[PDB]
Picture 1 (tube, helix red, strand yellow):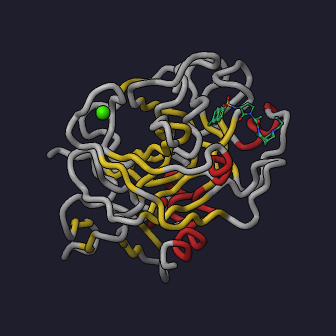
Picture 2 (cartoon, chains in turn brown, blue):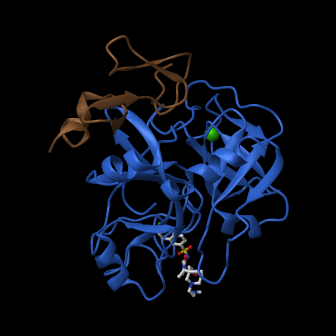
Length: 53
Length: 234
Ligand SMILES: CNCCN1C[C@H]2C[C@@H](C1)CN(C(=O)[C@H](C)N1CC[C@H](NS(=O)(=O)c3ccc4cc(Cl)ccc4c3)C1=O)C2
Ligand SMILES: [Ca+2]
């Protein structure tokens, strides 16, 4: 188990392999964080999250 | 939904309900964005005119979040066939945009390769709806959810009296009395990954509900991601 098969390549959401390295990305309405791994919601009520208020 | 649990406050915000002229639910849907609903093509022949209701968990009381939306355009897959339920998918564009709030939010659309390799290889998915709570029962007045294991493709083909196409997958239990049922059709099958919920299927058909040696059959959303993207632009 290497790259994306190894714990999702440390990505929050989408993981893909390019030239022996992990590339992370996010669903529409999220932006990739400065660390290139975490996904941050752009606005209120982002997709895929249960509502708290 | 047979078995499972009630959806608690805010737990199933992507659930939509297709309602007839008598204000009765007959099929489910999934909220994809402020203007679009995902559903089953077979549901479109079960009522003359219909609307879409969101933000509802109990059909017998007003909770404060309910909203009814009129349908502007119906986009049914052109290869849908009643004979086998192959290509059982449709998208609805609404006349007015959905205002997201408590109990009203979209589910995420995943990318194909990642969803097939990582989401569909998880132990379970989650199915939800207002359908019957047992095969011969009445429809539920409460929105319910149920964890359903992904089922081995060969095991499912062996269990089925009817063809399982490349556009279908199986989920549920061999003998345990938990499954989707009548009225749940067109509703969401979602998969949880790091506390984010992605659309993975559409409630499609089954040989009865929760029968021994039979599973629930769902439309394979990952085979239709390009189609969904195109339908949501026009
Ligand atoms: C009439 N049977 C001939 C074979 N059949 C023809 C069409 C294509 C498929 C094969 C599915 N069809 C069915 O009628 C299947 C076999 N059935 C039998 C009754 C059942 N209806 S239901 O309301 O109990 C129902 C609906 C959706 C479900 C979805 C899941 Cl995931 C699980 C159980 C369900 C039960 C049905 O669909 C139509
Ligand atoms: Ca209500």
